[PDB]
Amino acid sequence: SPEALRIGYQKGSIGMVLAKSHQLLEKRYPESKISWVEFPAGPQMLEALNVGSIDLGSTGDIPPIFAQAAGADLVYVGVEPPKPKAEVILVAENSPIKTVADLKGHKVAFQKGSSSHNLLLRALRQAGLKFTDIQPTYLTPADARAAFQQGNVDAWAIWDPYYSAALLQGGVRVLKDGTDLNQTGSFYLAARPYAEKNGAFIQGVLATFSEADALTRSQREQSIALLAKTMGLPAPVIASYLDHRPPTTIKPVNAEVAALQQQTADLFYENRLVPKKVDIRQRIWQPTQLEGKQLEFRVPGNENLYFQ
Image (cartoon, rainbow, N blue to C red):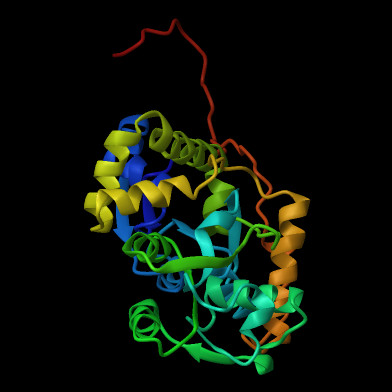
């Protein structure tokens, strides 16, 4: 284990947040200085990873494409399953819009460059539409939430927990979720030299986050109370939020996931969202457990006296 592990996490990095709350890493690795740094979103976290002020971070599938397209050598060390039920396009319940095709000509709010921008490009494409076929309305979630409530847009593409919060307030309906959109999953990233130097350690760390995520099922009451506090949201919103997640696993990134991530990188480059095509497979860490090298010798001679 290394001298220190500085972890970048977000409020929705469930494995990380539960591991932190339960002090699992501090207890498992008493010889490492474990530290936790909360970021407001993936891009800011990856900036920190890239200047070297943190060693391991959790983000969705989109932020890493931006960083890597800019030349960051950050590697994918682990992937979690996608959450198709947690990523949605919402309309008002009694909206005459019944399918994604019905969005043609309408105003749709979402954050530019976000997981919702990706969902929306893909959903529209299924229905034989492009962004030139609607009025894309680029807004961050607080600004979008207001516009949607005021009937200034007809649909809002957004992620959880905003989704669950809007849902419980009533009046809204999921027009489309990520289910048939073959989503990729969320990722854990590190700098390549740290991953290569600390292979066994990282694997154990990730395995710890996966154990911690499982507490949301085995200790649901306690975990809901924790996340209501840390996220600052009502317990029923957290309950809905957990109900939209599949069982979490953290695994090495396989060929299939790599190909899905490559598809998204291509989509983003094709739409000039990033300036470069990226070779996603070059950024996949093949797990290793490299033993550190030590230079050690012995001078035998007279009887060994243990200590004089």
